[PDB]
Length: 99
Image (cartoon, rainbow, N blue to C red; front, side):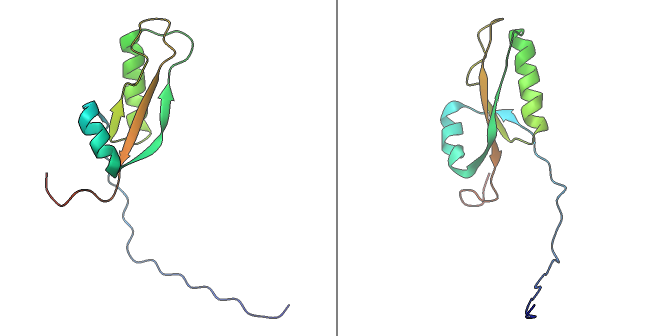
């Protein structure tokens, strides 16, 4: 076959060992920071669970999947909970450089 392939690779900067923790954000601030946050997916509870037990399971699970912000969108009923929690991951950019 007519020869003509090129391989242009170049790696010199790569260090991925930074892990952040997921926490519940105020809905107001959450919506405002969501502009600088990414969606890794929404989580849920199925079957039948205890309210706080499902919370803690959801919270750790979301954090386990590498989230920065977590929100209990639903699932705060009681036992018959088929709820959903919506989680966000921090982007690499944000408003200015200050905290």
